[PDB]
Amino acid sequence: TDPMVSKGEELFTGVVPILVELDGDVNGHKFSVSGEGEGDATYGKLTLKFICTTGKLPVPWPTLVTTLVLCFSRYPDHMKQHDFFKSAMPEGYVQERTIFFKDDGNYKTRAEVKFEGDTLVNRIELKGIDFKEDGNILGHKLEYNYNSHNAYIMADKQKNGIKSNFKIRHNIEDGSVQLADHYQQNTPIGDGPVLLPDNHYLSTQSKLSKDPNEKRDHMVLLEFVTAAGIT
Image (cartoon, rainbow, N blue to C red):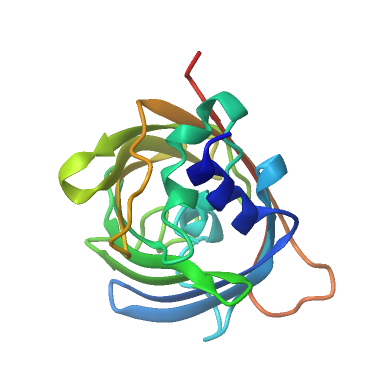
């Protein structure tokens, strides 16, 4: 048994409550999102409901899925020595992205993921610029659904963290695709040791739904993430 692995797995045993808080500004359209739910890392499983607390969300909900807790990914036993995300807990990590929407604007995000008591918290600031006010994002032309992806993870040694660059494809309501190229870096909040991984990937699937009794602008997310790519 690896005591560093045991430390991360004791934090994630059972069902862990999750809170997500985001403040955003996309082309000057300001908004806030609050999310709540629970994660069960044993099954790589997340269940979350997000509400736009400022009114109407000015971008499509699917474009925020990746921004809105990879510590809940299921790392196979033979790969648990590569789980940076849990190793940084409870002190947590910073997760930063630039997301380039092809032929449109970009989001830049900075988030802190850490425990507050029993609750795993994801606090995010999002800034979007250069969007077309008639494009697929500000024009709300994206279907309310989500595809399955693979995100390759690499060590980022001089940040004592990880980096990743992956593609997200959003279905457009005309049948086409809006690509969102993601560039990501994570770095620990604490000063203790973390697990720096060999190259691997995270395999994701997500299902978006609506709460039939909810009249606020919202998104229900069921998401599974599993690490793979190491023999």
